[PDB]
Image (cartoon, coloured by chain):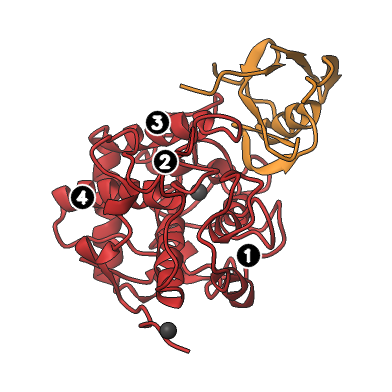
Amino acid sequence: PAAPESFDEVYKGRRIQGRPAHEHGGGYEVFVDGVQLHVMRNADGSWISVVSQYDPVPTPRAAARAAVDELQGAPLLP
Amino acid sequence: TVRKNQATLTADEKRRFVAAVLELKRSGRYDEFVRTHNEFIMSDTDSGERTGHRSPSFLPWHRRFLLDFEQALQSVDSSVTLPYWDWSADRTVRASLWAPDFLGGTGRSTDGRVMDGPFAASTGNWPINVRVDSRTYLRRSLGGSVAELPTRAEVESVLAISAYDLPPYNSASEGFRNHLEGWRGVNLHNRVHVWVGGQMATGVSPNDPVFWLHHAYVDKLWAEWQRRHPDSAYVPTGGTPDVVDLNETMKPWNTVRPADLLDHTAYYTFDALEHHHH
Ligand SMILES: [Cu+2]
Ligand SMILES: [Cu+2]
């Protein structure tokens, strides 16, 4: 499958970024305020992440936004 | 070893389970289970090597992980066994599971912090150490991100599926394993993680002790499936790249195969498990 497009935006006050590229070897990378958020693509082309692991979302940007939603302001840890 | 429905524990059994879990936390042993789980759920991938999740070995892998945890609990209090949470039956926030004498309740709405029970951060007895963000307090949002826990009718519809698993042996599969895991269909295991919320909905989900009770019920459902389908068994049985075949060993232990874990009775029984019937 094609790699998703990169993105860069401020969402709920935090900078979220995505780009094509202990954990699998990532084909796509997401960052929240510069700290990497581990994300993974599912067979059906949806995504999850460590911060929201059991609830598929359609895109890496959706996973970034879901992570920022759940973090409620907390810094991510590498 | 009899694994009991959580709702049926006596007050003394609840006390002894809680105390053993808090001692595994105090001694540093608990957190290494969280870390192992995190490592596998971040590594198991639909297009490559997959052992603990998204694959046929999801069920034997979690069976051996829960045995390692129960053995650690028995090393503290030999009387303790892992209880299970039948979320089809005990499906509201008022269930005794969530009382302050057992796991404590939901998180408060501002920051999702659990405020009562033995695992509340205010106790000083449940630091969240293995984590993905700065917060070090247990969080939950019961029923917050998804409305309802699975029902028994939904569980029965999954137990009725005859094939243990099916190619391509990942989150896209038809078959029992992937319906129980929940990536396709009505969704059992994944949805329960989402329903609890907080750390339980993340890749460090054993930070919530309810992790073990949920997985012990998922483990029971595998046993129930086997009683419903004595004629049907683990697949695949050989030569499958990236997937653990029946006679291959599983990481991280390497000394056990799915074949060694199909029959739970070599290790424990349940309070109740129907024999095969029609
Ligand atoms: Cu799980
Ligand atoms: Cu029969």
Q: Which chain is mark 4 on?
A: B
In terms of image quadrants, where is residue B231? bottom left
Residue of label 4: B71
Cα distance in 3D space between marks 2 and 3: 22 Å
Cα distance in 3D space between marks 3 and 1: 27 Å
Q: The orange chain is which one?
A: A
The image shows residue A3 at horizontal and vertical percentages of: 78, 19
SS for callout 3: helix
Q: Residue furthest bottom?
A: B278
Residue of label 3: B35
Task: Tell me whether the residue at label 4 lies in contact with that at label 2, contact meaning CB atoms closer than 8 angstroms.
Answer: no
Which three-letter amino acid code belongs to the residue tagged 2?
A: Val
Q: Which mark is residue A2?
A: none
Task: Tell me whether the residue at label 3 lies in contact with that at label 4, contact meaning CB atoms closer than 8 angstroms.
Answer: no
Q: Which chain is mark 1 on?
A: B
Residue at screen point 38% across, 32% down: B36
The image shows residue B87 at horizontal and vertical percentages of: 53, 67
Considering only order in the chain, which callout, 3 or 2, is on the residue closer to the N terminus? Answer: 3
Residue B99 seen? no
Cα distance in 3D space between marks 1 and 4: 29 Å
Which shade of the palette goes to chain B?
A: red
Considering only order in the chain, which callout, 2 or 4, is on the residue closer to the N terminus? Answer: 4
Is the residue at mark 4 in contact range of ligand 1, meaning its CB lies under 8 Å from it?
Answer: no
Is the residue at mark 3 in contact range of ligand 1, meaning its CB lies under 8 Å from it?
Answer: no
The image shows residue B197 at horizontal and vertical percentages of: 61, 48
SS for callout 4: helix
